[PDB]
């Protein structure tokens, strides 16, 4: 139980040592030991802490026997380097893609994790996620392409790989015109949809009552001209950045999009564009003039499924098929 | 328990860290402290409880969903059942009382299993293997919804949910109201799949008369007050047009942050007169369209009230956004956020207006509500509850809310199981012979899992102030002989449960007590995950706040 | 750890049932002296300092702060009787308090489960409504002489019984004025206006149809007496309107600043010309009036009243027939008030009062009550609302039921015959309602100074003879029937009193635990 | 909790409970803190430690029994080691610092076995069986020195004396201390060389002078001087004599009075005049009984009135006053006299005999002390110690006290061992050899007991600045090549690791108790599970 009230139940020894505040100066160094184990290999953070405490217990009796501390430190470094060559002869190389070696090693690596009983369908889940990215240069296999989305409610048995990019945030629903979208092109809007305003302070002076009649029509005409270029490209799905500085949506803008049945989801993270652009195969559109059909992708089904109070927006299939794909997995569970 | 442990000896922590069996002992006491509440509230013989905020207001809540929500529990493992009771409302909507007692009993009996030195993974596997066979056994003993010629189901489905509640004696009257309310609000999606939008039925709080005289409104009832008193209070005649507008009818400032600068003083008045004239342009298109009722999300300025009285139009202001969406689909109207179309011109189309039989505003006990009945496009329903006070209706509001979730599961899945301890007792005999096959260390874990489910049928007799053993001993006689009943319907021996009123064992099918099958699947899986997470905690670490 | 921070200790079992019954009995015990024509009065002290002295059941409960959680439910029962009907709020608590008092020796003694009792209370509630329906007789709702004796039922308890002869004429014309044909008369208290004027005499009063305003005239020349008044309601203030856009004018030429003030004077004169198109004799607005618009209306003889209450404008539109229009451009002759007359401003040292007299069926009336003191005048206001509430249920349904101890005992006799025929587990809780209906007729004897032992003993023997009209006198305590003296009360009052007591008894009997400290 | 206070025992929140692995870790570390304190003072290269008392008095000693006695502790496990060294000092009186190091060494090797999952009783069962195997092995290696005559028997007493005199302050005079400690037992002992009485030797310290002035004086040393010091300080016997005829009297000189409260009523002047003559006749009669008996120095327990100052001065009779009752027993033993209860029982056969009675001036002022010498071998030997510091005069007492405890243990027949770490190494390899034959679950129990015995030789190398690894490896390789067990650690660096040439000798009864006190104490400590400590 943390100081702010957050309670974390973790099997991994790294989180156990990180969330726990140790008053001893040297005992906190074990927290960063599991950090190096989790950053490089990612597995064995619990064993590396025990092996560190075991070597200290063996070297504790060596201090009273008249051995200099640097001799003890130089002895462990020479023994650790020799221990590396011991494991190099015993290990066996494996094929690029093998369902027998990868699945059995993934379920074994779980060990005491709560998902060990659920490892039946979860073991092929982690294997098939890495097999989508294959290289002969043995790259580190960046995990940014593999996105694990957490949803409150349900059971872990319902966890399965999604065939396309999943959206964490829900639809605006203010207009809520389209109920369900089939065979739609997902767009990406990096700009703001609103009546025309500069990014800096401006002034609008009305010297005649007949001028206000043109203002209300032209402010709606700008939002109308944006919908015209979108309709010509047949883009039924739009995604807009948060845009805390300038309003991203408007009641007059959502009403224009409701007539064309265009689904729009806002409040999207800025760092998630790389997962949206590469996963859906869509080039972001930051300008109404740069908007075209070539930058738009293709999606079979874009819908929002409300199940047991948990609302989620999922996309099924990607017709782009670019160089490398992405992995999307939705995580469900009873307890947060 | 006993004496407190020493504080951070050679451990050098700033908080409190306790290890050993003291953590699992306090984890059981955390679930047992929150169980003793939910225990006495289980079954038709259960009794309501009153929670006080110390501010002078009291809260009467029978089920443990709101009880655990209101009661503040700072124990780390105690918050699991608090979130589990809040969870049970999300998926099934009913069973918050049974899910807490079962999950607390699985941990209670497991406290003696760890003293055997049995590792929790053996205890967890014993509960999971017994659960996999339990879910399959429930699907074998289910009964079809066909039954006799007539329905004779949905009426009995609501009577089970009305149990444990003060209105349980009136369940015969409320049985026909819940069934007719859900069938009217049903929708269609996924190309033929019927959906049931729970909470679409309006629940109104009125005073006077009695709960037995509550009338089911054949349509939606909007809770709000009339704009102006000069408007006609009742509108008659067929094809009543209703306008739902989300746009502000009050006079608003020009743009947002601009500034109005006027040079010629002769235009000072003409510019200001135009600001008030643009607002009335949208009202002129509504009056010419023949809209009888104008529903507005926000308020309505006095400029728009004079046009509604002269045209005999009923204005309504301060409408909830979620309420107008149900009015649009029911009456057939289309929700209008603003007046515009693809063309540059601005006009109002008559297709956006709905139609119904009658619109009348009823006022009972300071509660003013507009009764919209006879929707042609899509039917709707509303229930007006009458009781002692508002807090007496707070329990009746959640009593009918849980009944809508139980009937929803029976129409989607026609598979139902009898209530009153039928499922909990049937799983015991099935797991007795199954545990002897596996043996080894998992035989005791499965045996304790079957005995842990006995808390539900035993709680029924304890709260009834009767002898529990004679009811349970005679209960097992039918279930123990049901597995050995053997093929040849003449089988029988199954679908029997406890009758707490008469103190006898009778068939639950003829008694009219049924429960959805999916309610048993989601309850046993959710109650197990709460016990698995607790049995796996070796050491609790509490860090003091800074 | 502490686990639950809210009432970690728990009181359950018979200890929680006694605390709920004992606290509920204490609510009814204080108002026992508040029932009957000889009933006493109760004075209450609020933290604000205002003194409220009345025998009404609801006014006593809502102004007392009860720390007992379950006893607060007894406080809200009178609100159900007051909002739905308004009469009989005292008999509801006495009946509901007696049920739990009679139902106490069951869970402790007979060990009967509450739900078993609830099933008996619901069956006894259905049979009680049938007995009340059988003893009820229809009467003519269009008879003015018959409705005067019905209003005196609630007046006999109140201090206004001395003026009852005068008070019936005030409440009769008040309900008949606001009612209209349509759910039948659909009369509402909001249309009836009761104005409290300190000083004067109670014997001298009259029903005035209109709205009594305390605002004075805005100009001395304004005529305070008009033979044929014409009322035009305007929600827009006569002051110069300012745009909410915060328009800033940049003045350059020397004639620009002088023209702005002239245009402000031209529009005020222009708005007066739009009003003078119909030539109204009176002007009434709910906002302030500028001093410039006052002179422009002096030539047309338009009396202007400012800062009128918002709800009063809707009451003016009913009596005068005028239509409320905010803009002066839409004013028409049809929107001008007509048929109004007898407009006069009476001079009183305290405040200036304006009178209106009427010649679309909805009307309104303003009752001027003159008391001896401000606090007694507050009592007549409460007594007038309860007097008009009796005539409401008479006009809704022709059904009329006896009162004064006849209806309560008529139910208990019918419950005694069916109790012996049940022969089951529900026989004991079924007899609790029969003894619970006896508290009301027994209370009338204790407050009258008679002997409840010998009177109630012979009273039950009378109902066995086949007559349901035998009541209990409030003065002499005679067993003479209520047909002679004429006590009668609407059936709705008898039904709402029994239904509320049964629904409230089942609520407190289901509470097995009392916990606090939640602080939501 | 259910909402009601749950209290099983009074002072609930005051008392604490320890259980599991944390309870065992706190017990081992409590002994390691005491061990590292004692390991620094173990061996002749060790160092003393200052003991500050709450009253302000200071104590400087390396003795594990004295350090832990005045040590104020908190944890009860460290308090069990206090009575461990106290058990060694009370009975044997030698090796108080070795029982603490050996006991903690058993607990250090037991902590490693507990972490491996061994039940604590199985650990205690292995130490009990290994304790008897080490004692039976060392018992066969030693030889009986009782075959030598009394001339060579004195040499073995000088060998074990110089060993116990080391490791303590003022160890430069150990050559003379070893000679004086043996001559005390030579004078006081049984003719059969058995069951010598230790109580006949008293330890009397004196603050002043230098350590070189310490010498043996056979007799009684009293803090009281001669009454009425007009008499010569040094008393000399008559020309011919049988002795000095020392007199000891527990009765003060007074006219006879009843023990009960009495009332003497004088009713006439004649009765008062008779009391005058009766008064002086008793003081004249008491002084004549001593002169007729030939006695010279008179010792009084309660003293006497100033009337007898000049009376005893005329007859040249020395006298002392206010002598303690415990010192009167010490006087009659030295002079072989008999205490005379009254003058009527006074005879010449009950008078003591000593060589000379005299007093020393000591320092400038200080106080006057009486000294008695004997003319031949007697049953009383009083130790005389001088020093330039109060701390030196104190520690030298218990330094020679522990030295006398080693000599009296050699009086027991057929028990001798050689020190210098040669005993622990010999018994260590005998236990490790049995571990290979037994195997089983107890195989690791004999390994922990073998590694614990080697801690004492390795501790000696720490204080001497040597390598404990290279020193222990030489001793283990020597016992495997040759059967000689006399090779051990040399902290003085004189070479010749054979203990026979270095003369270092220890009692076997002292080394046997070190294993028994350490093994039997760890058996009780490992059984402790729940620790309930109330707040002070």
Image (tube, coloured by chain):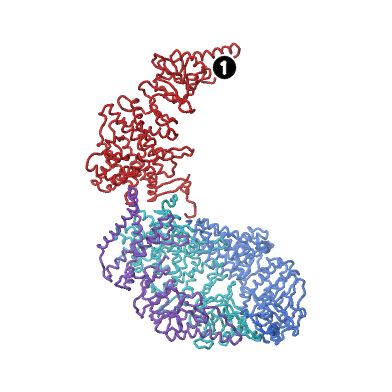
Chain colours: A purple, B cyan, C blue, D red
Number of callouts in the render? 1
For residue D433, which quarter of the picture? top left
In this orientation, does residue B453 appear? no
For residue D331, which quarter of the picture? top left
Q: Is residue D283 above or below residue B387?
A: above
| Closer to the camera in the image, B126 or D376 | D376
| Closer to the camera in the image, B445 or A103 | A103
Tell me residue C498's x, y (percent).
58, 66
Q: Is residue C134 above or below residue D520?
A: below
Tell me residue A162's x, y (percent).
37, 74
Point 46% across, 13% down: residue? D289
- Disc 1 is placed on an element classified as loop
Q: Is residue D211 above or below residue D376?
A: below
Tell me residue D69's x, y (percent).
42, 38
| Closer to the camera in the image, C13 or C505 | C13
Tell me residue D313's x, y (percent).
49, 16
| Closer to the camera in the image, A114 or D30 | D30
Q: Is residue D287 above or below residue A130?
A: above
Disc 1 crowd, CA 10 A, few/some/many (<14, 14-19, 20+): few
Relative to residue B491, is residue B77 drawn left or right? Answer: right
Among all residues in the image, which is located at the extreme top?
D270
What chain does mark 1 sit on?
Answer: D
In this orientation, does residue D528 appear? yes
Relative to residue D257, is residue C48 drawn left or right? Answer: right
Q: Which residue is mark 1?
A: D264
Relative to residue B212, is residue A294 drawn left or right? Answer: left
């Amino acid at each position: 139980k943390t100081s702010r009230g957050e309670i974390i139940i973790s099997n991994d020894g790294h989180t156990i040592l990180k969330q726990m505040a140790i008053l001893h100066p040297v005992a906190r160094m074990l927290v960063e030991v599991s950090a190096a184990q989790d950053s490089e290999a990612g597995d064995g953070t619990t064993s590396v802490v025990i092996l560190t405490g075991a070597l200290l217990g063996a070297a504790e009796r060596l201090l009273n026997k008249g051995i200099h501390p640097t001799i003890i430190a130089d002895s462990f470094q020479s023994a650790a380097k020799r221990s590396v060559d011991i494991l190099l002869e015993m290990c066996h190389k494996v094929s690029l893609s093998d369902r027998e070696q990868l699945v059995r090693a993934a379920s074994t690596s779980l060990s005491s994790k709560i998902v060990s009983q659920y490892s039946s369908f979860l073991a092929p889940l982690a294997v098939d996620s890495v097999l989508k990215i294959s290289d002969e240069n043995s790259k580190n296999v960046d995990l940014n392409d593999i996105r694990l989305v957490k949803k409150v409610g349900g059971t872990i048995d319902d966890t399965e790989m999604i065939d396309g990019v999943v959206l964490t945030q829900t639809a605006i629903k203010s207009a809520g015109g389209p109920t369900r979208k089939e065979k739609a092109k997902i767009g990406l809007i990096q700009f703001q949809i609103s009546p025309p305003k500069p990014d800096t302070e401006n002034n609008i002076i009305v010297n005649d009552y007949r001028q206000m009649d043109k203002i209300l029509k032209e402010e709606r005409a700008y939002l109308l001209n944006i919908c015209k270029k979108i309709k010509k490209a047949k883009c039924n799905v739009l995604l807009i950045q948060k845009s805390i500085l300038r309003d991203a949506v408007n009641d007059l803008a959502l009403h224009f999009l409701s007539k064309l049945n265009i689904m729009v989801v806002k409040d999207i993270e800025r760092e998630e564009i790389e997962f949206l652009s590469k996963g859906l195969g869509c080039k972001p559109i930051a300008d109404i003039e740069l908007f075209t059909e070539d930058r738009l992708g293709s999606a079979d089904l874009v819908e929002e499924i409300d199940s047991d109070g948990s609302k989620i927006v999922r996309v099924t299939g990607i017709r782009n098929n670019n160089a490398r794909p992405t992995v999307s997995v939705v995580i469900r569970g009873a307890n947060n | 328990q006993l004496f407190n442990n020493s504080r951070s000896d050679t451990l050098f922590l700033g908080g409190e860290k306790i290890s050993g069996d003291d953590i699992r002992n306090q984890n059981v006491l955390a679930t047992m402290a929150v169980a003793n509440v939910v225990k006495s509230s289980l079954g038709p013989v259960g009794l309501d409880k009153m929670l006080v905020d110390d501010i002078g207001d009291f809260t009467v809540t029978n089920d443990g969903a709101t009880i655990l929500s209101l009661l503040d529990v700072q124990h780390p493992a105690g918050k699991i059942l608090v979130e589990l009771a809040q969870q049970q409302d999300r998926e099934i909507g009913d069973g918050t009382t049974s899910v807490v007692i079962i999950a607390s009993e699985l941990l209670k009996r497991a406290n003696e299993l760890v003293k055997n030195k049995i590792h929790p993974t053996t205890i967890i596997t014993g509960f999971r293997v017994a659960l996999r066979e339990a879910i399959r056994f429930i699907n074998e003993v289910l009964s079809t919804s066909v039954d006799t010629l007539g329905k004779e189901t949905l009426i009995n489905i609501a009577k089970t949910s009305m149990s444990s509640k003060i209105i349980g004696a009136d369940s015969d009257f409320f049985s026909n109201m819940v069934v007719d309310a859900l069938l009217a609000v049903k929708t269609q999606n996924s190309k033929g799949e019927i959906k049931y939008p729970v909470k679409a039925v309006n629940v109104l709080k009125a005073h006077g008369k009695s709960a037995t005289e509550s009338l089911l409104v054949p349509g939606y009832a909007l809770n709000c007050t009339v704009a102006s008193q000069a408007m006609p209070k009742r509108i008659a005649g067929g094809n009543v047009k209703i306008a739902c507008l989300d746009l502000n009818l009050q006079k608003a400032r020009m743009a947002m942050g601009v500034q109005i600068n006027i040079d010629d003083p002769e235009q000072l008045e003409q510019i200001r007169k135009r600001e008030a004239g643009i607002v009335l342009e949208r009202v002129k298109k509504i009056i010419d369209a023949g809209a009888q009722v104008v529903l507005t999300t926000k308020g309505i300025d006095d400029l728009c009230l004079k046009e509604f009285v002269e045209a005999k139009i009923m204005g309504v202001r301060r409408c909830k956004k979620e309420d107008l969406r149900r009015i649009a689909r029911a009456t057939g109207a289309t929700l209008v956020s603003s007046m515009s179309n693809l063309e540059g011109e601005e006009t109002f189309e008559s297709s956006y207006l709905g139609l119904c039989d009658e619109v009348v505003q009823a006022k009972f006990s300071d509660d003013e509500c507009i009764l919209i009945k006879g929707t042609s496009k899509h039917s709707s329903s509303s229930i007006i509850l009458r009781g002692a006070n508002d807090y007496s209706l707070d329990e009746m509001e959640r009593s009918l809310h849980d009944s809508l979730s139980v009937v929803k599961r029976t129409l989607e899945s026609g598979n139902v199981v009898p209530g009153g301890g039928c499922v909990e007792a049937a799983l015991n005999i099935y797991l007795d012979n199954f545990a002897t096959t596996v043996g080894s260390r998992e035989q005791l874990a499965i045996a304790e899992f079957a005995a842990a489910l006995l808390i539900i049928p035993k709680t029924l007799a304890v709260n009834a102030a009767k002898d529990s053993s004679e009811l349970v001993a005679k209960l097992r006689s039918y279930h123990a002989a049901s597995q050995m009943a053997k093929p040849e319907k003449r089988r029988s021996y199954r679908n029997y449960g406890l009758d707490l009123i008469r103190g006898k064992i009778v068939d639950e099918i003829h008694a009219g007590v049924l429960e959805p099958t999916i309610s048993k699947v989601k309850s046993l899986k959710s109650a197990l995950e709460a016990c698995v997470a607790i049995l796996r905690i070796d050491t609790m670490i509490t860090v003091d706040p800074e | 750890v502490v686990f639950m921070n809210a009432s970690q200790e728990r009181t359950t079992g018979r200890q929680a049932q006694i605390s709920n019954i004992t606290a509920a009995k204490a609510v009814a015990d204080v108002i026992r002296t508040c029932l009957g024509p000889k009933a006493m009065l109760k004075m209450l002290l609020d933290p604000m300092g205002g003194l409220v002295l009345t025998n009404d059941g609801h006014a006593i409960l809502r102004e007392i702060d009860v720390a007992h959680p379950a006893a607060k439910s007894m406080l809200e029962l009178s609100r159900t009787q007051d909002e739905e009907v308004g009469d009989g709020t005292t008999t509801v608590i006495i009946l509901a308090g007696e049920i739990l008092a009679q139902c106490a020796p069951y869970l402790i003694e007979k060990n009967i489960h509450p739900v078993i009792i609830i099933q008996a209370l619901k069956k006894a509630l259905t049979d009680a409504l049938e007995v009340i329906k059988q003893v009820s007789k229809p009467v003519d709702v269009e008879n003015d002489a018959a409705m005067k004796k019905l209003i005196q039922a609630s007046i006999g308890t109140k201090y206004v019984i001395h003026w009852s002869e005068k008070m019936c004429e005030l409440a009769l014309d008040a309900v008949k004025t606001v009612r209209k044909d349509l759910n039948f008369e659909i009369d509402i208290k909001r249309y009836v206006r009761v104005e409290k004027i300190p000083g004067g005499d109670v014997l001298d009063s009259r029903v005035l149809k209109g709205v009594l305003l305390n605002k004075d005239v805005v100009h001395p020349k304004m005529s305070r007496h008009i033979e044929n008044p014409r009322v035009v309601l305007l929600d827009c203030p006569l002051e110069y309107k300012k745009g909410e856009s915060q328009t800033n004018i940049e003045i350059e030429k020397e004639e620009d600043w002088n023209r702005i003030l002239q245009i402000e004077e031209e529009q005020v004169q222009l708005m007066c010309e739009q009003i003078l198109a119909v030539r109204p004799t009176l002007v009434i607005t709910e906002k302030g009036v500028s001093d410039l618009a006052q002179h422009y209306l002096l030539k047309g003889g338009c009396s202007v009243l400012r800062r009128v209450k918002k709800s009063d404008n809707n009451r003016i539109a009913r009596v005068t027939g005028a239509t409320i229009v905010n803009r002066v451009e839409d004013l028409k002759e049809s929107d001008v008030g007509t048929n109004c007359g007898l407009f006069k401003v009476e001079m009183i040292g305290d405040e200036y009062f304006s009178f209106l007299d009427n010649c679309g069926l909805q009307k309104a009336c303003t009752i001027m009550l003159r008391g001896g003191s401000k606090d007694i005048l507050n009592e007549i206001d409460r007594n007038l609302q309860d007097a008009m509430a009796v005539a409401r249920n008479v006009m809704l349904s022709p059904s009329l039921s006896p009162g004064g101890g006849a209806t309560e005992m008529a139910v208990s006799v019918k419950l005694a015959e069916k109790a012996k025929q049940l022969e089951g587990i529900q026989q004991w809780p079924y007899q609790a309602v029969a003894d619970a209906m006896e508290c009301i007729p027994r209370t009338l004897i204790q407050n009258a100074g008679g002997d409840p032992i010998r009177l109630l003993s012979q009273l039950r023997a009378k109902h066995a003879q086949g007559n349901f009209t035998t009541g209990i006198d409030g003065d002499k305590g005679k067993i003479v029937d209520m047909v002679s003296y004429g006590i009668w009360e609407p059936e709705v009052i008898k039904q709402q009193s029994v239904k509320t007591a049964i629904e409230s008894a089942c609520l407190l009997l289901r509470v097995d635990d009392i916990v606090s400290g939640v602080r939501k | 909790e259910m909402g009601r206070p749950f209290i099983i025992v009074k002072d609930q929140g005051n008392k604490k409970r320890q259980h599991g692995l944390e309870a065992k870790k706190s017990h081992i570390l409590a002994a390691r803190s005491v061990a590292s304190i004692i390991k620094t003072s173990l061996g002749p290269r060790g160092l003393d430690k200052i003991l500050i008392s709450p009253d302000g008095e200071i104590t400087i000693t390396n003795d594990g029994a004295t350090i832990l006695s005045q040590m104020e502790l908190d944890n009860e496990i460290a308090k069990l080691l206090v009575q461990l060294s106290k058990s060694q000092d009370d009975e044997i009186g030698d090796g108080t610092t070795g029982v603490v190091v050996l006991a903690s060494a058993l607990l250090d090797q037991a902590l490693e076995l507990i972490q491996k999952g061994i039940h604590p009783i199985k650990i205690a069962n292995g130490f009990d069986e290994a304790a008897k195997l080490a004692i039976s092995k060392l018992e066969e290696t030693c030889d009986d020195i009782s075959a030598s005559n009394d001339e060579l028997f004195r040499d073995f007493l000088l060998r074990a004396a110089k060993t116990s005199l080391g490791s303590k302050i003022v160890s430069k005079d150990h050559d003379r201390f070893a000679e004086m400690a043996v001559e005390a037992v030579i004078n006081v002992m049984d003719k059969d060389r058995k069951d010598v009485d230790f109580d006949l030797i008293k330890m009397q310290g004196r603050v002043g002078g230098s350590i070189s002035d310490s010498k043996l004086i056979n007799g009684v040393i009293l803090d009281k001087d001669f009454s009425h010091p007009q008499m010569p300080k040094c008393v000399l016997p008559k020309e011919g004599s049988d002795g000095v005829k020392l007199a000891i009297l527990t009765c003060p000189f007074e006219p006879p009075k009843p023990k009960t409260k009495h009332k003497l009523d004088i009713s006439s002047v004649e009765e008062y005049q008779k009391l005058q003559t009766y008064e002086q006749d008793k003081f004249k009669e008491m002084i004549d009984d001593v002169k007729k008996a030939g006695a010279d120095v008179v010792i009084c327990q309660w003293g006497f009135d100033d009337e007898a100052n000049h009376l005893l001065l005329q007859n040249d009779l020395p006298a002392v006053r206010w002598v303690g009752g415990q010192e009167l027993e010490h006087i009659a033993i030295s002079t072989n006299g008999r205490i005379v209860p009254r003058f009527q029982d006074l005879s010449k056969d009950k008078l003591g005999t000593c060589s000379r009675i005299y007093e020393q001036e000591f320092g400038t002022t200080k106080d006057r002390m009486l000294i008695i010498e004997q003319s031949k071998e007697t049953k009383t030997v009083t130790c005389f110690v001088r020093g330039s510091n109060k701390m030196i005069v104190d520690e030298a007492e218990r330094a020679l006290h522990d030295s006398l405890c080693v000599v009296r243990n050699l009086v027991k027949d057929s028990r001798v061992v050689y020190g210098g770490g040669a005993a622990e190494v010999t018994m260590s390899l005998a236990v490790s050899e049995e571990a290979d034959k037994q195997r089983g679950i107890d195989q690791y129990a004999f390994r922990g007991f073998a590694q614990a015995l080697d801690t004492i030789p390795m501790t000696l190398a720490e204080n001497s600045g040597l390598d404990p690894i290279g020193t222990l490896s030489t001793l283990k390789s020597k016992q495997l090549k040759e059967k000689i067990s006399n090779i051990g650690v040399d902290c003085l660096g004189y070479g010749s690791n054979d203990m026979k040439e270095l003369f270092v000798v220890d009692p076997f009864i002292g080394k046997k108790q070190q294993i028994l006190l350490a093994t039997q104490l760890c058996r009780m400590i490992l059984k402790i599970d729940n620790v309930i400590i109330s707040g002070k």
